[PDB]
Image 1 (cartoon, helix red, strand yellow):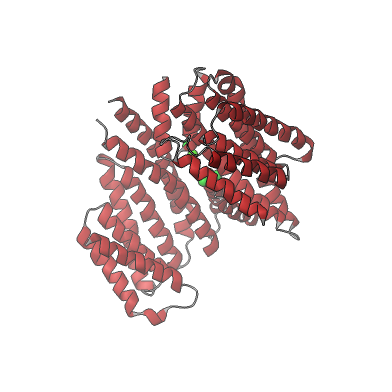
Image 2: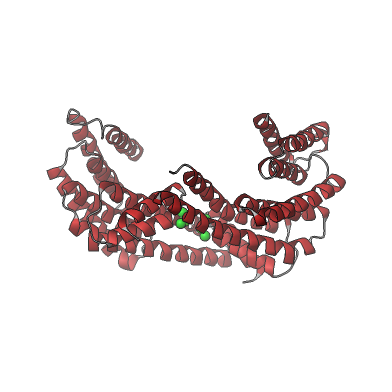
Length: 230
Length: 227
Ligand SMILES: [Ca+2]
Ligand SMILES: [Ca+2]
Ligand SMILES: [Cl-]
Ligand SMILES: [Cl-]
Ligand SMILES: [Cl-]
Ligand SMILES: [Cl-]
């Protein structure tokens, strides 16, 4: 009921691996209208990542099965219908997150760190809608994802250090957007490489707190470069 | 809606790791009242094992947290445990109702009789893990009686290397160790099952050797742990 009580409840749900309970708790905290602490922001993000992620993973298995059944018209129809059922769940999750971002999280974000984080998150959830969209609505959704990422990108470039894990994480996800959604491997590689190289160049300005996360994300950036290069 | 379609939906749901959907499909298949095939009963078993399993795992983390508290936090942990318990009991009672109404009555073979009686033992055991005081003694006896009848039929009708007989021995030994706190009985049961399987090891066929030997390894791992 109370804010602090809902946060302790979310942490308990996290430990129980009951992420729908966790998402419900952090949604309620967000809806109280106060700016989320760094802890609360991370709890919200973890909760919804796991809720949407379960559907994404399932949709990837059912869509793959649907495509890899040629002659079975009845079996393919079942897979198609189950895929659509899963899509509807996924869309409702994404729309709940995107509504929270638009109504509470983005307008209340009083620091560049926070604003970049939430705009990146907006980019991610429009990207998850884009993964699942049919041709008519897809171009619009893809553009919404790109615009969110692009605004996040410009703010992080202006306000944040190249080694900042949120700036690096944005570069990772935006490069993935270009590769997987926009089919633009050259743009994806150049964004990823530039982010990696800028972090390498400013290796002095990197504190002992965000020293691990930063270097882990840099490794992921370069892993994508080597993968996409072949 | 038709059995064959529901079975295919269950398999789809399994691939998707959507186990509530899978359990719902196999529940409705069972409720048509025809004896389940080997494939169908295994789908039902996997579905509900995962559905109850999620609650059991959650109940193991929230119960522990409640234990290690000194406060408002304890009452929150208690109430969340109780909520998880309610879900868990409703799952177990669904499975146990399917077992009483459909599965155990229609079981035409000793193999399937043992399979379902073991299952009955398992789901009362999961209720026993979560019971306190009055109800527990009664819950524990139902588990034990299900296992005991299964055990007698398996010894009579199945070879020591049969995976269902071995799996029963494993779960019944775990019942003795974890529910009845009878470690000597648990070890004796597990040791006998392992040794008897080792002694008749030419009585396997190329199909079931992998499952049998995996359970044998789990039996011995428990013996090593429990010593
Ligand atoms: Ca859940
Ligand atoms: Ca599920
Ligand atoms: Cl949940
Ligand atoms: Cl969950
Ligand atoms: Cl499900
Ligand atoms: Cl599931």
